[PDB]
Amino acid sequence: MHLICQSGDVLSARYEIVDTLGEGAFGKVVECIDHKAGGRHVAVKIVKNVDRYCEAARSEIQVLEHLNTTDPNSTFRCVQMLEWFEHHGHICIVFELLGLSTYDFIKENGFLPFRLDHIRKMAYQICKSVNFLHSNKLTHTDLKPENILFVQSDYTEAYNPKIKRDERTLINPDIKVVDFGSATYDDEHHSTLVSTRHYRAPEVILALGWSQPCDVWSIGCILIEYYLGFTVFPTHDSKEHLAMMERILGPLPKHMIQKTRKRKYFHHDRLDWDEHSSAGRYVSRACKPLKEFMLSQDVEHERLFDLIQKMLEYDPAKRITLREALKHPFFDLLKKSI
Ligand SMILES: Nc1c2ccncc2cc2cnc(NCCCN3CCOCC3)nc12
Image (cartoon, rainbow, N blue to C red; front, side):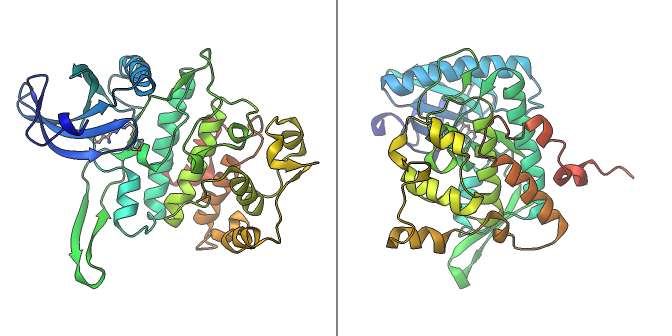
């Protein structure tokens, strides 16, 4: 793919690459000048020339055709696909150019969190956008800060010599949801593994089956990450992941522990985890009950955390819906009209 995506390369006799926006395992996203739409800047995802990413981009194109047609004004904040083409046997998908991923925005400010006012606006929009997928018999499955992007370059940035980086200050926090290559329809076959490990629901970890509620878990993890500036589940390993959930959210429902065929992780009805090993005293030291991450006892911080705690309900049958979520008191402040 190195061979086909340099600056100055022209795709489909119109898209001139000017910059790289994002890399990763699926392939590359590049900024292009569209010489056939009056020099409008767009994004083109170049898909890695492999079975996996080919069929996932074929599916993504089908999903976007449906979302974009159903919601032409993008009221529900899903990215607009403009077209797709083939370039040296890679699928390329053209998109409206958005601003920074929320991931890159936090990362490049030294992992400093978003303001509560911004998080309220962003959480509302994420919940409204993914509730639209929910309404339309879809689950995203891979919600994570890399897949939430600012609509606009609506920030200022200044070089701060004291700390030798640009700091970027958000003016307007409006977002859209991207990447529908994993999005699964209610009646389609359901992959065993889904989500980036840090945002993966407990029912996905435990192979108990999944649908719309696994997205709600992911959003929960996103929101605390926006509030703190870092993931509360940093780990690579599922048993440590489950130890961290226990430390932060309490014990897992016995029914989930006893039902799972991933019995590898467990011993009788307990997590099989030496709490007193140096790896367990790590998790203990690293993790505290969820409500202790609060930076303020201020009621608006209490509203957010009550929502976050509902999103991280272990039992996906009991987990809050985005329908209910949009009605949570954390959002009331958005609906002020006196
Ligand atoms: N980075 C993207 C844009 C940047 C600017 N404007 C429009 C964009 C549209 C995109 C549409 N799709 C994707 N990515 C698909 C999945 C990539 N994610 C998940 C993996 O980590 C990287 C981000 N990225 C996109």
